[PDB]
Length: 49
Length: 49
Length: 98
Figure (cartoon, rainbow over the protein chains, first blue to last red):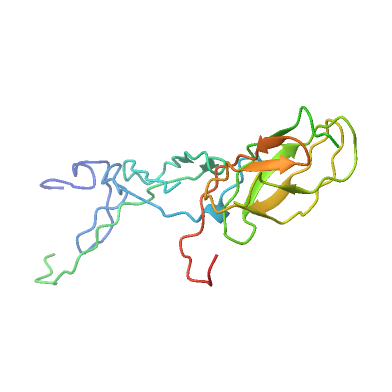
């Protein structure tokens, strides 16, 4: 009510926050580059599609 | 085959990614970067209130 | 049969020294009956020693060639045909000699 910067409304990305050690929940970027090594068995076969 | 997928780390979006392959059939994923997690080591220095 | 107007084609798989290669085959012939099969010369072990043939039917067979992607010929008791497939093999290959 004599607030500085309310980071759950002004932390870049799209973040809103709870009580946190230093975490910014709910950010709308912060991109996690995921790379998967998928075994060929887990697929659907190309002749069964 | 080995399905890379980077998307914005955005909590509430099911981005429904695709393994492009011709050995086997392309198979759907959802690489949904749900909830921004950050969480480093911390130290409580002082409560204010 | 004279296995004429035949086709062996794409159906893909995962390829293994044993009998991992597969290829569906539109076996088409001018007679119907039994058919011993193997690639024109020794380059493959065919799981199915002999394959039945209808005239314009299709029967997938099993084989192993050596080729990871099996574009290996199959000499179907008069008439060779490429029994194509694009097959990515296992990641590991420590078990005894091919």
